[PDB]
Image (cartoon, rainbow, N blue to C red; front, top):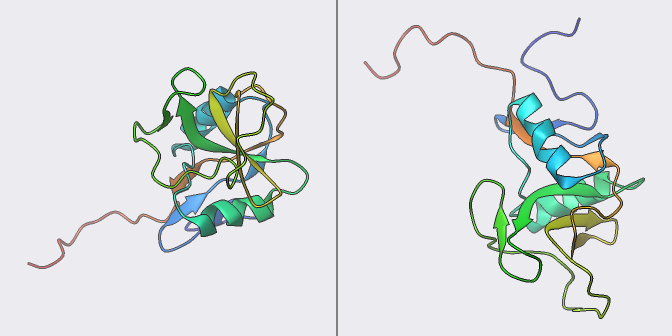
Amino acid sequence: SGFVCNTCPEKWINFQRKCYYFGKGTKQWVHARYACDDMEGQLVSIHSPEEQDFLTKHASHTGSWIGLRNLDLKGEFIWVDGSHVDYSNWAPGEPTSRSQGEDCVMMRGSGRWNDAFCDRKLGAWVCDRLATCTPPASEGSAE
């Protein structure tokens, strides 16, 4: 068994004290958020062009799922965390013409997001959660 203070091995990525999940599985957005709960995290919900690009680059064989869920379809996109989008990446500026539905947002290898029905065609689930490094706080800091 692997030691603690290090849960993110390959896909999963840890930083200052938080980690990301870029694993493979499921086939729907709702399945991604459910996966997050299993890891005790959250549906990514990327807010940094770097982070979105980070997973975007990490996701080659298939796109990735983010913490984005829209009301109906073309309405307002709200994050699974209950926070309206701030940057958004669904296409740089191409409104396309093939309108069929978009209840969630996906990420393509192109280097951004694509707003389309949660039931598109992905293969990798991504969620974020804090690292597994948390020792029992005994001595109170700053006495």
